[PDB]
RNA sequence: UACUAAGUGGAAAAGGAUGUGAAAGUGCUAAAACAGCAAGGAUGUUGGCUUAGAAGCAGCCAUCGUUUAAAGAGUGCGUAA
RNA sequence: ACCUCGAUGUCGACUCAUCUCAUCCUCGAGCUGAAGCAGGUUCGAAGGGUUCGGCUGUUCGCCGAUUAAAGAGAUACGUG
């Protein structure tokens, strides 16, 4: 089996939801129930490779590099790291890392800040 | 088969051997075999 | 490297005896004979339930022998104590095989029926009509018989057909 | 390097002697994603986990006042669980992990300083 | 290709290139150079081929220097004619190469890149080439 | 006294090579390496642009920060994805 | 411009050929942009064979029909 990445909310048909070992009626109802208000964002999800697809449903935090407009105060210009239009503050970065801390595989705050900054470095933006 | 005065490895798994006083190469791909030089 | 790697011995029933040319091991399934060429500087001495060997002098050929005959001796010991098996996956729409006494015969896409002779001390078993297992006392004979039977319908990448070495993975190609 | 190995000997001897209780267990054929999940579980815990060579433990275990040693690092993937307080949570974590595995393989160590079997250490962590 | 524009003479004699090299026995500008271990005669077309290979394998990151230039012009009498009747006509320009002197040099690029560039340029020359580092 | 195994010796080039002997220091090693075998080989990331499919791998950006003893917008093979 | 002018008879055709392999076919093998037929390419190989006619004196060349093919060359550009 392969990874899944589906929109948060109602999705009766999926890329593979009829031959993975689960019922779509028994899946999409709870998928939408868990993400009823969280609709309209490309949310990362994970499907288990286990043979019975036991109920261990998990969700991740909203992706970085699409929300960098709030954190670094820019309008998504050239993607190179040699051109820049703005600077990232400390308060926005701390808030976004605090929100994304549940996505990490470790319980540490400054590490979360550095991870989010390094991911945002795709734009070439660094803390001033 | 391939005949060329110079033989060098071309992939990551192109090994070189000396068989019957002739240099040769062997690989997992049939488009890499070479025997001369 | 190999050659100074100590060789274990089986003193329950298996035993060894060396000559100027004969090195014979005797175990539960027959005997294995290794006939060395004359004038070999590699010297053999065996302790109780232990075997250690070495070349007396330093030459390239001597060092080659020092590993090669160690490998052949351990191969012979493992064979005489267990006996080796070769599993052949016979894949095809109509290809099959079975045994008529001393003859191992097959059904191919060939107009002429195909048969093969079994050397002495070799056994074959057809547990299912599309697979062969060939059991023997030394890897040399079983490998020779396997490559003798393989020489008809070598596998092709366009479709898995023929005789396979049981995890000899076939690399497929574009079937158009 | 060798001087780095000596300095690591001194460092790990200091780290082991700073505490009093520690258990080494074998969790073999494991994975790295579950390992960073472990690092998430132990972050609250004051203890930690490390992977370290056989000879260094052989020369450092007799300096940290621990006895009962014949194999300090052998037979599978090797780590260390040195708990300076609240090792309970770490032991519960490792117990759940070996539940996710097939069987328990005790190596050495004790909860508070006297090498003891796992027949009761498991119940301590259960 | 690389050719002088005028000369006080139109058809000079040939030159021997026996003995050790004269001038350009050590690198000047580039970091890694290609020395020749045999004296011979090389035209400007092979120099052009080596230069284009160097540039293509180099990229717009490093620099290269050419150490020689054709200053001589031999003759080649047209085909199927009898002997005599003065000298023939020039049709190429050649630079004499003495053994033990450098031909091309490169700098400002990683070691593997420059090594492969010089090796690629070397086979285009009719002389036995050899790599060389800056003397420092 | 050493050497080559080629009948080179007893015809020859550019090029190619775990053929072989000698010399110089070179990085490691019995606090155990090389070779092989047992595992793992990760997170932001199926990030974002575009390609009705490219999402560790049509192509491109950054090509970094963290978990760690160990891991790469992944060494590549291989998937519209 | 080395041997020949005190003579060494020069193309092609006819008959008869012989030799080399850098293979035209038959033969064995590898790779494949080899599904199978039919191919392409490279290696090994000289036992045998490698067509008949129109044009032109012709080799060559063009054309027509066959076959397995209608090979490359040499022998004072084989041999008055």
Image (cartoon, coloured by chain):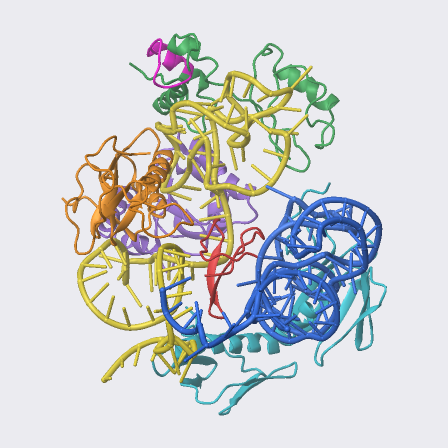
Chain colours: A green, B red, C cyan, D purple, E orange, F yellow, G blue
Q: Quadrant of residue D99?
A: top right
Q: For the point 38% across and 23% down, which residue is it?
A: A118
Residue C93 placed where, x, y %? 82, 53
Q: For the point 50% across and 51% down, which residue is it?
A: D119
G52 or C26, which is in the foreground? G52
**Can you say which quadrant of the picture contains the C terminus of chain E?**
top left
F63 or A111, which is in the foreground? F63
Q: For the point 49% across and 92% down, which residue is it?
A: C20
Q: Is residue B37 visible?
A: yes
Residue C31 placed where, x, y %? 62, 84
Q: Is residue D36 above or below residue G79?
A: above
Q: Is residue A114 above or below residue C144?
A: above
A101 or E116, which is in the foreground? E116
Judged by its main secondary structure, the magenta piece is loop
Q: Could you tell whether E121 is left or right of D117 in the image?
A: left
Q: For the point 34% across and 42% down, which residue is it?
A: E46
Residue E107 on the magenta span:
no
Residue B22 placed where, x, y %? 48, 66
D53 or E26, which is in the foreground? E26
Q: Could you tell whether D10 is left or right of D111 in the image?
A: left
Residue F38 placed where, x, y %? 51, 53
**Can you say which quadrant of the picture contains the N terminus of chain E?**
top left
Residue A87 on the magenta span:
yes
Q: Residue furthest bottom?
A: C20
Q: Is residue E34 visible?
A: no
Q: Quadrant of residue C123?
A: bottom right
- Provide the residue span drawn in magenta: A79-96
Q: Could you tell whether G43 is left or right of A115 in the image?
A: right
Q: How many marks?
A: 0
């Amino acid at each position: 089996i392969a990874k899944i990445n589906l929109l948060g909310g109602q999705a009766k048909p999926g890329p593979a939801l009829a031959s993975v070992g689960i019922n779509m009626g028994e899946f999409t109802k709870q998928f939408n129930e868990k993400t009823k208000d969280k609709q309209g964002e490309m949310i990362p999800c994970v499907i288990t490779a286990y043979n019975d697809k036991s109920f261990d449903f998990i969700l991740k935090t909203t992706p970085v590099s699409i929300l960098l407009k709030q954190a670094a105060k820019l309008e998504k210009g050239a993607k190179n790291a040699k051109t820049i239009v703005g600077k990232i503050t400390m308060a926005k970065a701390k808030e976004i890392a605090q929100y994304k801390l549940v996505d990490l595989n470790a319980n540490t705050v400054e590490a979360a800040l550095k991870m989010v900054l390094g991911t945002a470095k795709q734009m070439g933006i660094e803390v001033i | 088969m391939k005949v060329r005065a110079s033989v060098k490895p071309i992939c990551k798994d192109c090994k070189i051997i000396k068989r019957h006083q002739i240099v040769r190469v062997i690989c997992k791909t049939q488009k890499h075999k070479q025997r001369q030089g | 490297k190999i050659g100074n790697r100590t060789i274990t011995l089986d003193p329950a029933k298996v035993n060894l005896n060396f000559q100027k040319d004969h090195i014979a091991v005797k175990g539960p399934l027959g005997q294995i004979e290794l006939k060395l060429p004359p004038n070999l500087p590699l010297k053999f001495e065996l302790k109780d339930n232990n075997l250690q060997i070495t070349r007396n002098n330093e030459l390239k050929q001597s060092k080659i022998f020092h590993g090669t005959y160690n490998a052949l001796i351990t191969n012979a010991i493992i064979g005489v104590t267990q006996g080796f098996e070769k599993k052949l996956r016979l894949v095809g729409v109509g290809y099959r095989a079975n045994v008529e006494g001393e003859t191992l015969n097959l059904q191919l896409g060939y107009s002429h029926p195909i048969k093969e002779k079994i050397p002495k001390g070799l056994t074959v078993k057809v547990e299912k009509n599309t697979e062969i297992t060939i059991s023997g006392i030394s890897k040399e004979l079983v490998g020779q018989f396997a490559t003798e039977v393989r020489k008809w319908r070598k596998p092709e990448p366009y479709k898995g057909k023929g005789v396979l070495y049981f995890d000899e993975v076939i690399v497929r190609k574009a079937g158009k | 390097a060798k001087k780095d190995k000596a300095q690591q000997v001194a460092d790990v001897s200091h780290l082991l002697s700073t505490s009093a209780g520690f258990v080494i267990f074998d969790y073999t054929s494991m994975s790295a994603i579950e390992a960073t999940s472990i690092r998430k579980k132990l972050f609250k815990n004051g203890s930690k986990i490390k992977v370290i060579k056989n000879n260094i433990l052989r020369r450092a275990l007799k300096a940290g006042k621990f006895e009962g040693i014949d194999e300090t690092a052998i037979k599978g993937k090797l780590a260390v669980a040195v708990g300076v307080n609240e090792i309970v949570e770490t032991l519960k974590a490792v117990d759940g992990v070996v539940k996710a595995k097939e069987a328990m393989n005790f190596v050495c160590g004790y909860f508070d300083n006297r090498a003891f079997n796992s027949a009761d250490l498991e119940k301590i962590a259960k | 290709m690389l050719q002088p524009k005028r000369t006080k003479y139109r058809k000079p004699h040939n030159v021997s290139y026996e003995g050790k090299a004269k001038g350009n026995s050590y690198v000047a500008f580039g970091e890694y150079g290609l020395v020749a271990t045999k004296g011979n005669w090389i035209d400007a077309r092979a120099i052009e081929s080596a230069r284009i290979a160097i540039s293509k394998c180099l990229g717009k990151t490093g620099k290269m220097w050419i150490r020689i230039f054709p200053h001589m012009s031999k003759t080649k009498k047209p085909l199927e004619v009898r002997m005599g009747s003065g000298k023939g006509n020039p049709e190429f320009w050649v630079a004499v190469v003495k053994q033990g002197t450098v031909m091309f040099e490169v700098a400002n690029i990683p070691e593997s890149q420059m090594i492969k560039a010089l090796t690629r340029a070397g086979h285009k020359l009719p002389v036995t080439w050899k790599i060389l580092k800056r003397e420092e």
